Image: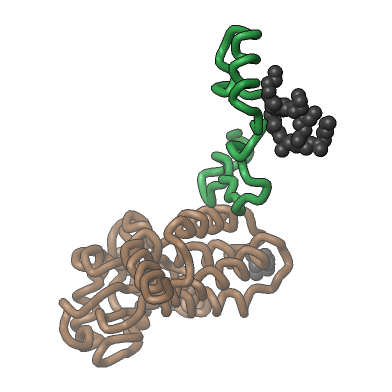
Chain colours: A brown, B green
Amino acid sequence: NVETVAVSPTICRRGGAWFASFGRERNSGTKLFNISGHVNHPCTVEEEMSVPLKELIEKHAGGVIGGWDNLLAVIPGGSSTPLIPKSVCETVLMDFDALVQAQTGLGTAAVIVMDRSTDIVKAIARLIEFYKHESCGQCTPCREGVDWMNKVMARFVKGDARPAEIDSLWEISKQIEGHTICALGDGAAWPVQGLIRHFRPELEERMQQFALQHQ
Amino acid sequence: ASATRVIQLLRNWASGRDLQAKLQLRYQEISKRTQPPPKLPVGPSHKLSNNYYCTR
Ligand code: SF4
């Protein structure tokens, strides 16, 4: 990676011990963070490795638009990392191990925040559409399954599905994950898994609204 | 049955039972030859999840 290559001369000049003095053990150094989405001051900043998420957001991004209580979910490490709700983001550290313990993973340390005034399902479906348009199509699991999940999420956004299809989509994501040539399939299955795990009531309520309004 | 009463009593006495109670020729008591459409439910393996064939 560009950052990995760029930090090496400084590591050599200042010594590895100085770089290891930052962060936690197995999580040493400093990281570049990209905060985007629903913050007052989206920005790119370099900060100590195991920084708390809320402290990072408040000190650098100016806070969440409408306050911290207005926060709904955060994508901490780019589109390939599963989302976490506000409760997890309250006391979560920004490093590999602690974010894996949160079932997310650090990824590229790209923080995408979402307040309570936005459609989480629509954003996840947009990410799945991005993965559908970016898959190379070499292997059948990624190609066919990601197209399938794109269609399923498009139906989910309108509520045109039935509640029994949420588990079917979860099983499809399980089938895609770990069975592809590269990690694009994993990076497409994970956002769906996180969205289901943390917002199944939202999907069910959307489906029932569609069911009553269409009879 | 379009049988007169005298013949009815004669056959009842000859056989020794009551025959109009149990007749051997079908009449309007049978079902209609035109029936409403059915629905025919599905089996237990028609689930959308947790339905891997290796487990059944
Ligand atoms: S998983 Fe990777 S290799 Fe397979 S089709 Fe998708 S992008 Fe291509």
- Residue at image x 43%, y 67%? A81
Q: Quadrant of the C terminus of chain A?
A: bottom left
Q: Nearer the viewer, residue B12 or B35?
A: B12
Location of residue B1 in the rendering, given as x and y in whole percent from the top left corner? 64, 31
Location of residue A205 in the rendering, given as x and y in whole percent from the top left corner? 33, 67
- Residue at image x 27%, y 83%? A117
Location of residue A47 in the rendering, given as x and y in whole percent from the top left corner? 29, 78
Location of residue A129 in the rendering, given as x and y in whole percent from the top left corner? 55, 78
Q: Nearer the viewer, residue B56 or A114?
A: B56
Task: Give the side of residue A180 with respect to residue A90, left or right.
Answer: right
Q: Nearer the viewer, residue A148 or A186?
A: A148
Task: Give the side of residue A22 with respect to residue A66, left or right.
Answer: right
- Residue at image x 16%, y 77%? A69
Name the image quarter holding residue A85. bottom left
Name of the residue lying farthest toward the bottom? A41
Q: Is residue A13 visible?
A: no
- Residue at image x 54%, y 62%? A186
Against B4, residue A9 (above or below) is below
Name the image quarter holding residue A55. bottom left
